[PDB]
Length: 121
Length: 121
Length: 121
Length: 121
Image (tube, rainbow over all chains, first blue to last red; front, top):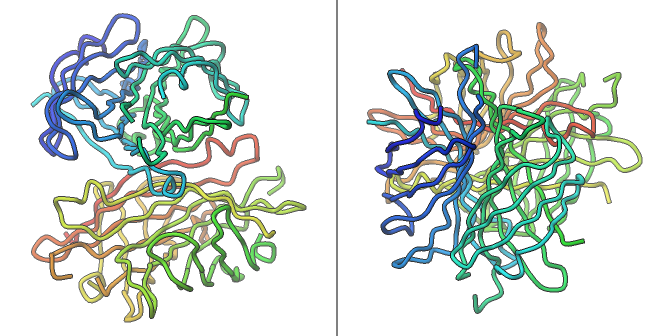
């Protein structure tokens, strides 16, 4: 985990994120998207639970990206929750929630759910 | 948002979290739980999209908590995605994803989904 | 369960559904909504697992509503997954997924997630 | 849709389901699983919204399976929400929610979320 998490990851839709896993569970980095009301790089921050593992389990982690930078303000944020699996073909399998700021009447339709798999290749 | 987000929040199951919303979209603080394989305070980190709003919309945000501290290591992490609504009865309405580290065979049953509403009272 | 499930249920946003729980796990009825690109009554069909319970557990169930009737065709469908709890204040607590038909490019943003609590009152 | 939906579908984990899409939005069939506290065939019932489409969109649908049959009673039910895409490589992309009957104290951890892609091959 940690060392193995640090680096560049890519998902099936063309997004990329670079992250550094800190010794004490922190995850800091940048996310550059391919889809959405996104344009360029956004700051990401998260945590991972290591001290993950004598039975080859994945390392649980999660991170958040607020979709605001100097070129775009999408009034939304996405959180990814999943686990890191290392080795030959290391990957981070996740499920995500994207919430957009709405008025109280439309709050019932403010959150989208999806999944993403990231690889080092 | 920000100023209004900073402070202590409580949810329906008895959990509490104290957070500081930084000028540039950061959210840092601690989460003390009431349920789970949790015991005491855990570090939380997240982001919010302000620059939220001429039509009274909520401010989108998200945060992560890795369930590891000096007393417990639950090998899991939770991410909350939702929005902040301020005023008299300010609240943060969220949906969350809790992923536990599993072996590849049980990865299909590694993530729980739920919702939480936090208030200042 | 079953007998206790049969009847009219109402949720916090003003929607109502009438359902009949059949002896062999079937759920059939109609849903009349309050929100969305919905207008009038829609057919609902689902299943419940009874034979639910010596430790006062809820009865798991789920149902689907395709949002098409003689007055509206929203090109979407919602599924609710949750459990029935009977007694004085019987309720059905659920989480739902609403998927809209999209082109392949927008499939990543086709599903909304939410929760609903239904009561007999 | 409908005609194209009728038939046998398989997912990445080895489960199979046979379904008949009825002229008026009904979906009826059987699901045979590969994973879980499942064993053999279970009844499935659902709905689809056709009258789906001059811009090649998918057809929204959803179905439910209560995990009880003559050999197993798992006290749980799963609902799948997604869309059907036809053609050469027709597929049904879905997100699912699996709720297990729990006591009120553990209701917060009663629902799992995941995704499944089904193909005709």
